[PDB]
Image 1 (cartoon, rainbow over the protein chains, first blue to last red):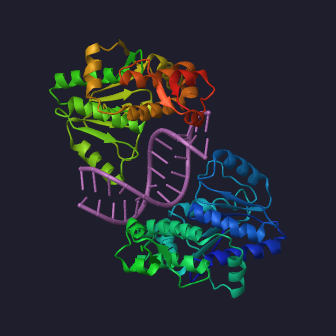
Image 2 (image 1 turned 30 degrees about the vertical axis):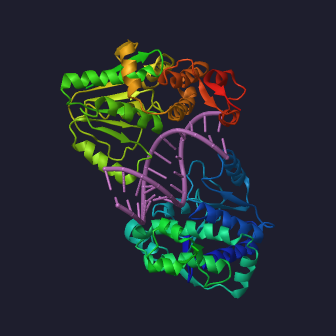
Image 3 (image 1 turned 90 degrees about the vertical axis):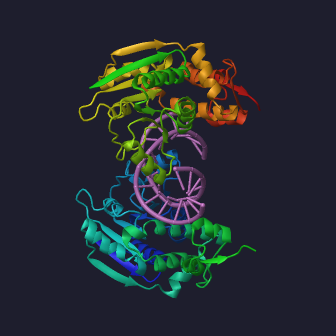
Length: 256
Length: 256
RNA sequence: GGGCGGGCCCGCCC
RNA sequence: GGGCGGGCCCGCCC
């Protein structure tokens, strides 16, 4: 397994990095690309499918797959993806139940996994039964402590590292194809905020840095970097970031 | 070291009385030095059992409620507490088993069959530990019996002591009077049992035509009107998929 | 001791 | 789509 890790300045930029990477692979392989792309939350998984569809609906079949997909539909698109020699399966850390897919070229990871163990489980889906394979972990600056934890804990090193700053061209291409409304982007980012908040201690993250960055994804996606997430003073209490400067950095109070 | 027995009652509901009587006896004989685990199929039913057992033995013993929908903090504490207690009854579902090794447990009671054939073993493991003696009592009803035959054929276990049980009018009144729950709650409770039992029919070779009406009849029995059926909407009956079924007519009273 | 919310997943049934 | 049971991680209040 040829493991690599693409670091970006902002969490959001991991999205672009991934889209670009996919475009390159499709061009080189003439649309003979079959990859699994993992995501931290269900809402963010669906969000990724939209983008990937708007980008590569024509070239590849984009498959959404997570816990909140009904069992019938889950059984059918596992069978389908087993058959497909081309397509991208976007999913969360779903159970291995019957997740043995042949001829998978790459496993992509946008953002760290919920728990340290899953990193191993994810890359297992490629380079099996003799075939070659690659893994690409797209993270941001503030997620880095995860890689260190992979070594100290599970004793795994990622040989190839690389920085990434997105072109103004790619940012516009992606964001333009985003049809979701602000209320949906908020739901999406909040699910990320909660996910990342849950794995701070485990990955020795810096709360004061990581949360604001994740939240900033809201503005970045709505093409207004300095626009913060609108919430009620009550909702903020419900998150427990009410009297916190981190909260003032992440959110815009609107209780009037 | 495990003295296994099984008390068969005519109706599911009667297993409740059988258990309460059993517990009273053990308390009398042991002068309240009784420590037992009593397993239950659903959460709501577990809580319902705690109410009864509290009204019956709050003075003599500590009654502890323990299931998946108990918050992790409260779960850590009452595990510690029960480990320490030399007297008390833990009412729970097939929870855990993350460190569920409780010392000096005298009996494991089981009201109704377990969800999985395997769990029967797991449950009785909690007694007769590290040399000490222990006993198991399985309270079931006529229609659950196929479970015992399945235990032999599959798991190759035989329960030596059997006993048929028909409750006195005295005990029925003692228990039911202490029940503070309202009819809407008794409906919620029985429905959880209806669904639990419906999920383990094929596995235990139960007769749907017999077992479900019996479980549902628990509603009347508890409200002291044996022929009173469970009130539900034609919509709710469709949600369960027992709409055009005679079994549904036997279990429910339609109010569309 | 009591109350409440959030992220991910698994098993079984209709 | 719904139901029953369960696992892991996180936050808040008294």
